[PDB]
Length: 84
Length: 48
Image (cartoon, rainbow over all chains, first blue to last red; front, top):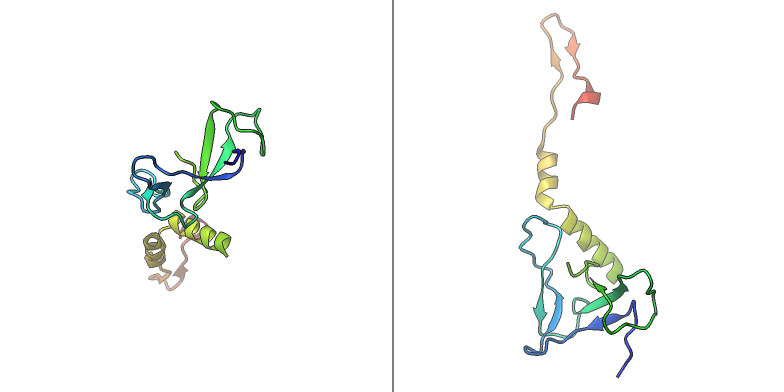
């Protein structure tokens, strides 16, 4: 049991499926050819599963305690793309 | 190096290969001999 911090990679397991949220790297690419899609994958290994936390609010900073109900922005480790 | 691999993959996603191939396939306009014999030279600052 670890205490979450800003700017620290986190791995999410979907409660029902048991799979892990990630960037698929395969994109329908409509409108934005550049962006990828986001979906579940079974395997834990890989930089796709991990997402980097960042403080959306200006008051919070890197390494700060994570609030219970603060707004948040997450960046994919694999391609440095936000969950958008 | 994973960082270099990620950067190259990002650039590949940015720029499609087919567009580069097509731009290379584009052909320049051609200098030609005129009737009087001089060479009409297209202004390159206004062209491909």
